[PDB]
Image (cartoon, one colour):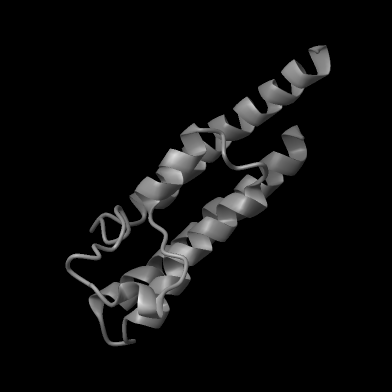
Length: 121
């Protein structure tokens, strides 16, 4: 149908906007602490601590398969990256501190993304 195509153009445009949001969030992590999944070879207990691991490469795979239906789902994954880190790593660590700085900096990008998603529909 024509509606299904219009829908798919919206999903495609959302994917376009979320791709740009993802790039901007990831620039706030120049150390690449959140770039890839936590290694289960190097942290073999990780899943005993963290039940839903997340990272930017995993978010990008979902994104490129148009797996985010709306901004809320994308924010959920970004918040997992942060929140997982802040639970697994202690407050005095470079990892925890990196998550705080990413949360703080990402806030600004996410604020305007919500406006753009509402605004453009």
